[PDB]
Image 1: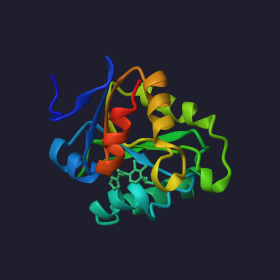
Image 2: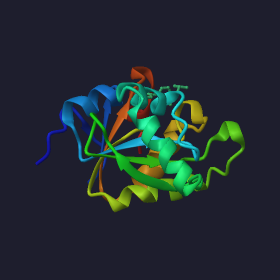
Image 3: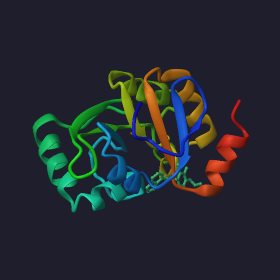
Image 4: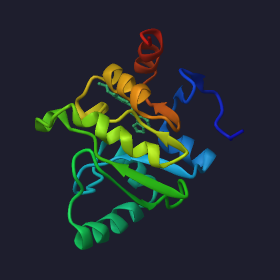
Length: 167
Ligand SMILES: CC(C)Oc1ccc(C(=O)Nc2ncnc3[nH]ccc23)c(Br)c1F
């Protein structure tokens, strides 16, 4: 039993809700919140900008030190950093950004990072400003993640479309 509330169950392990991931993280304080990161951990907009804003820019400060030490992530890769006031940990995961021409096949690799964590609060990878089809992202999520994932979808219209079209 966990503290996530109001989710629709899609499969044995995947759950979905129309919610602002920032507000959901603040309420649940999950062990792991997933960020929709880029390889430079520049949290300017989208989910990343919102999460970073909620940490009062502490996420960005920590991220800049991470990059200075380690260099950029790989597309499809991830790193574990602090969750600040939102979660114990933040798993920064880089899905391919279609608006940069990146290979959509890397979306499966990106979701594989979730399997290293028993339970996660997450957005749909490569959705929103990353330019992929969120219906496809949900399909890859369900077919790749085996651990327990609670998906927050900000847009109510998109949420209803994802549910109603789910196979
Ligand atoms: C073309 C348009 C429909 O694309 C999208 C628009 C918005 C979302 C969305 O709800 N994003 C979020 N989800 C959870 N927390 C969040 N905090 C801040 C944003 C946010 C998504 Br997934 C989209 F794909």
